[PDB]
């Protein structure tokens, strides 16, 4: 069934999915520094408390880059869900920058570094709560882009 | 959290139109996934009927395409099924089901189903059962004959649910008259006869028939 | 595309290993799934992409195969594993299912307890007589039940019903109902049902004479 | 055999997808190398200069190098095995160099931080191995892209 | 399987003009189309791929559009360096059939040719053949009438013409006319004249030489 | 830079076998990309011949399939082309080209080409050219040139003063005379005040016959 036109659909849905999964991986990098590198460079181990002011700045850079790549996402079909992650990335980046009072210093404590970018422990006052539904908003976007690719492939085998 | 529930009339006259609705909770049909209707006649295997995606693309079984249609009400998070010009071959347990990509990217697999509802195609009129005792004559067997009812199902209990051990409620049998009939028996110690009363509680919802029957020797 | 799976019925004990084969007619790749269905319940997806386990499915389930021949394997069968199993292709609609395989738990031979029930006087007033023969708690499922009215074998006036295998002792129960008109029933005296079963060295007959106690 | 072409397409789809995960992880290390080395959050612009304190930014980048080595280990493809094992070794060598130079790598000097995890620097003694697995993934990413394209190429052939 | 029809075959426009080239496919090829620029003697240079995407290095004044069967290459702000033959190409399947091509000439204000005549060399003469060469340098348009006169007798069927490709900088042409005679026929006359008629010349320009 | 270069004989007798080799530098045919042979007759359009991928898959033009063969030498980073039972319809400039995905994911686009080599299918024998001076008339801009006569097959290359003279040079396209041999002229305009002071030498190269000729062009006395 219209094999030459389907290949364009499959390729188009591929590019959209790839661009979302790239934003996905940037989020997973923000997660890895949160649960593996917060307050911890050594011969063994690959403990040092209360000094993460740099690690916070690097993760702020990733969050900006996440917004830039989201602005480059243009697909008239996924427009509903793209703008959701669009403004979700905005409230996140703004939140860390909104209060530099505990994030724009060299010695940010563990309970504050775990607070802004670690979505695991209990306290999520200023920070990781906004990281929370930014991840979830990309989950929605990633699933939709996956299903659009599957539906394009599904068009091949139709009777 | 993902739950699906079918509903709609369970009896349709021959050449009539079947109508069923699937209510979804814990999930939104407008955001993704394919949603399908699946068929299973009594004692037989499964047959896929149709499917739809929120973009509007719907597919139908080529053996039923002429008679089947599926509609979507995204505002109510429900979808329906219509089957016109039905015959007795359309009698089946009807499922609505969701399909998901799971850990893959192609194809979709059915991972969520409703409980299913039985739809019967027959010219028989709804009728409650006539309950007759199977009087007993160290172990004694007594039962209840549930005869000439329509349509399925009939729930039988003993002593308002107090007697569950030893109970056997046989599956119904479609008699040549078009009506169903079954028996529910229980084995009790022969010494308990004349001391314990045995009541079979027969319930037939599709006719609002509730019957209690004393079974004595 | 048609899917034929075999065997239609399996009989194995708890702890045994069973394999079910699903054969596709012109090629599936790996777009095959395996379902488990208990009586009265919706089918439960076990394996997709013809070797991938679904979340929650235990490791004792395993599937394999690509293109035409697929196989589901249950090593170390558990009590909860006895159900009906279907294979399904997902490469294209109508997503054909197999006709299914039902695997029941194998146990030792159990003879049935045979009971006969004469028609009730209440039912007789309506003009119909129903004689019920009951086979209780036996194994295997195979059992021949014959109705003899005045020692004449009956045909075409009886129906049979078998329970599902009991989840507690792995036995079956069978009922046979001989339905006659009130006039036909009152014209004979001896009503007997005859049971032939592997657990019985010879057929067993339960009889009663109409209008006696 | 349109079904067999379907599996070829979606299979090389997943490989390219998993390879681009490693690719995007590297762009994060690259982004924290060119936009957050010696830095902290400001109000108006978002980031302001903060010299000589990057002992946690390097610790952060180390976990991604560990995460990168993890994803490269999980990559299983008989057609891409050559380029897969080339990136695994370059991933092992990189994380080994960061742990080998732990004397000068709290608060690593921006001269050392730019030297250790930044591609655009002259010295690159503590970075040189960040280019040889970036380019190794580049070669890996291009090969997976061409494998997907070749699968789609089969769809339209006489 | 699929044929590509390119229109027009020849195109002539001025610097700054806007021009359009159409490529038509016998059936749908989606957006799998490419446009090439082939300068004389050089290999094709990719301008646009996937039928609207500008290849890196190519100026923005090149633009493509279309999907399916209709396809259009548009060159805005035409430049003298844009003289080439342009080809469309489908790439959905092999063989990736090319279009027939479109020749694009850059129009230019009228420029008169400088005319030169060249007598046969003493080296060539003793071989038995005499070649008299007439040179038309840096003129436009292409149309030029070159006639040979030997002792005021118009020659025919003993001369051959060769024109250079359009200059990529000044958009001009150059032409050569070689009159070939035998040594015996050459040494039988005295005056050899080249007469050039061109729209940039108010009257035909003659260049001649005697044999001494 | 990525660079492709075809090589091989430019004259093939009819019914013979064409053979060309593409040498690739700056890239590796074993690593990726599709590699193709493309054909362009004098004056006509382009015709794709065949392609290959390092996986082994090889496609040929259905119009040529019976007589075309592409070989690959990954150890030498070269690949070759073989055309058998050749006729005049096979005379063309032959290109080897690379295909690439560019910024997309399908299909591959031809983005790198070789310079192209010209192969002529003919029974005629190779013949080097005769070079003669187009002396400048003693009459300001002056014109001088070189006449390249009676050679076969194409092409001939002409330079002036070993390349030190490029501005003002016109090498005209070759012309096929009725004798079956080609003829060509190359001219250059120079200041009239330079004659009798500066030397002017045209360099003529005809590789089919290994002919290197330098000719001094001076005003006749």
Image (cartoon, coloured by chain):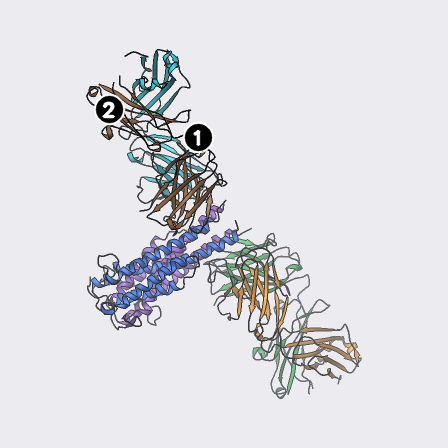
Chain colours: A blue, B brown, C cyan, D purple, E orange, F green
Residue at 60% from the left image edge and 57% from the top image edge:
E3
10 Å crowding of disc 1: few (<14), some (14-19), many (20+): few
- Near-viewer residue (E40 or E171): E171
Name above or below for residue D25 compared with residue E61: above
10 Å crowding of disc 2: few (<14), some (14-19), many (20+): many
Question: Same subunit under labels 1 and 2?
Answer: yes
Measured in 3D between alpha carbons, the distance from the residue under mark 1 to the one under mark 2, in whole angstroms, is 36 Å
Instruction: Mark 1 or mark 2: name the one nearer the start of the chain.
Output: 1
| Residue F127 position in % (x across, y down) | 67, 68
Is C192 positioned to the left or the right of F158 in the image?
Answer: left
Chain at tag 2: B
Question: Which residue is denoted by mark 2 in the rendering?
Answer: B198
Q: Which element type, helix, strand or loop, lies under badge 2?
A: loop
- Near-viewer residue (F59 or B17): B17
| Residue B27 position in % (x across, y down) | 34, 49
| Residue A39 position in % (x across, y down) | 22, 63
Is A35 positioned to the left or the right of E204 in the image?
Answer: left
Question: Which residue is denoted by mark 1 in the rendering?
Answer: B123
- Near-viewer residue (C115 or E112): C115
Name the front one of labels 1 and 2.
1
Name above or below for residue B201 compared with residue C155: below
Residue B66 appears anywhere in the view = yes
Is F137 positioned to the left or the right of E69 in the image?
Answer: right
| Residue C89 position in % (x across, y down) | 43, 41
Residue D103, quarter of the rendered image:
bottom left
Residue at 46% from the left image edge and 51% from the top image edge:
A152
Q: Which element type, helix, strand or loop, lies under badge 1?
A: loop
Residue C120 appears anywhere in the view = no
């Amino acid at each position: 069934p219209n094999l030459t036109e389907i290949s364009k659909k499959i390729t188009d849905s591929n590019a959209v999915l790839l661009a979302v999964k790239e934003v996905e991986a940037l989020l997973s990098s923000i997660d890895e520094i949160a649960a593996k590198a917060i307050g911890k460079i050594h011969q063994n181990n690959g403990t040092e408390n209360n000094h993460n002011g740099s690690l916070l700045a690097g993760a702020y850079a990733i969050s900006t880059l996440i917004k830039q790549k989201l602005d480059g996402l243009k697909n008239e079909g996924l427009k509903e869900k793209i703008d959701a992650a669009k403004k979700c990335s905005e409230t996140f980046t703004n939140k860390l920058k909104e209060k530099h009072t505990d994030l724009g210093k060299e010695g940010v404590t563990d309970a504050d570094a775990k607070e802004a970018i670690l979505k695991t422990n209990g306290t999520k006052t200023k920070g990781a709560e906004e990281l929370g539904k930014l991840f979830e908003s990309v989950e929605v976007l990633s699933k939709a882009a996956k299903e659009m690719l599957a539906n394009s492939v599904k068009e091949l085998t139709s009777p | 959290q993902v739950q699906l529930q079918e509903s709609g009339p369970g009896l349709v006259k021959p050449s009539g139109t079947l109508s069923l609705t699937c209510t979804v909770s814990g999930a939104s049909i407008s955001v993704g996934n394919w949603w399908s209707w699946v068929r299973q006649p009594p004692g037989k295997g499964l047959e896929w009927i149709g499917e739809f995606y929120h973009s509007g693309k719907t597919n139908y079984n080529p053996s039923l395409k002429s008679r089947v249609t599926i509609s979507v009400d995204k505002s109510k998070n429900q979808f329906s099924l219509k089957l016109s010009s039905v015959t007795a071959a359309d009698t089946a347990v009807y499922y609505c089901a969701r399909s998901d990509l799971l850990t893959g990217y192609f194809p979709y697999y059915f991972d969520y189903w409703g409980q299913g509802t039985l739809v019967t195609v027959s010219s028989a009129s709804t009728k409650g059962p006539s309950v007759f005792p199977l009087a007993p004559s160290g172990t004694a067997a007594l039962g209840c004959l549930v005869k000439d009812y329509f349509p399925e199902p009939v729930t039988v209990s003993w002593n308002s649910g107090a007697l569950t051990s030893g109970v056997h409620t046989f599956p119904a049998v479609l008699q040549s008259s078009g009506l169903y009939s079954l028996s529910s028996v229980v084995t009790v110690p022969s010494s308990s006869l004349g001391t314990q009363t045995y009541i079979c509680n027969v319930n037939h919802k599709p006719s609002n028939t509730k019957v209690d029957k004393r079974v004595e020797p | 595309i048609q899917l034929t799976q075999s065997p239609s019925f399996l009989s194995a004990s708890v702890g045994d290993r069973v394999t079910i084969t699903c054969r596709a007619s012109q090629g599936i790749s790996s777009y095959l799934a395996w379902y488990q269905q208990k009586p009265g319940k919706a089918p439960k997806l076990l394996i997709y992409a013809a070797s991938t386990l679904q979340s929650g499915v235990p490791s004792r389930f395993s599937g394999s195969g690509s293109g035409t021949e697929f196989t589901l394997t249950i090593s170390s069968l558990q009590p909860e594993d006895f159900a009906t199993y279907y294979c399904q292709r997902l490469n294209s609609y109508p997503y054909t299912f197999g006709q299914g395989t039902k695997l029941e738990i194998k146990r030792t031979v159990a003879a049935p307890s045979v009971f006969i029930f004469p028609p009730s006087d209440e039912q007789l007033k309506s003009g119909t007589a129903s004689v019920v023969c009951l086979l209780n708690n036996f194994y295997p499922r195979e059992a021949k039940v014959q109705w003899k009215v005045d020692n004449a074998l009956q045909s075409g006036n009886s129906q049979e019903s078998v329970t599902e295998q009991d989840s507690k002792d792995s036995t079956y129960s069978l009922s046979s109902t001989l339905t006659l008109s009130k006039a036909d029933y009152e014209k004979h005296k001896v009503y007997a049902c005859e049971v032939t079963h592997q657990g019985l060295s010879s057929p067993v007959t339960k009889s009663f004479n109409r209008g006696e106690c």
